[PDB]
Length: 122
Image (cartoon, rainbow, N blue to C red; front, side, top):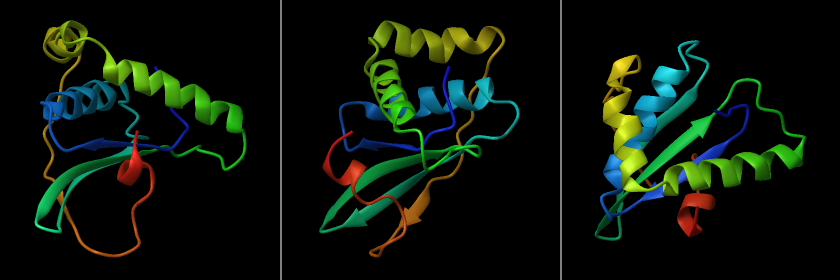
């Protein structure tokens, strides 16, 4: 469990869709307060379309860099987690938790999203 920080995830292939939907379901279900400010949008440019997800908190502060790294590694591992746990925490979570599949937002050429972290690397 973690929050109060801004993080972005990139996905262009490698069955990443599973992680995006899985992580989105666990986070959404784990955060019933609806304080989670995340979303998933699909970008299509240069003849190539890529999927990008943006996750932001409410109490998120500009200061406290020590927290940035904490969430960075925390989310990094949680996402890289083996398929066993990735699928279990996604399906087996049906016990008490759940998952939702919201509509993907279209992305265009401009300066809005993070356009930096997901553009380079997680």
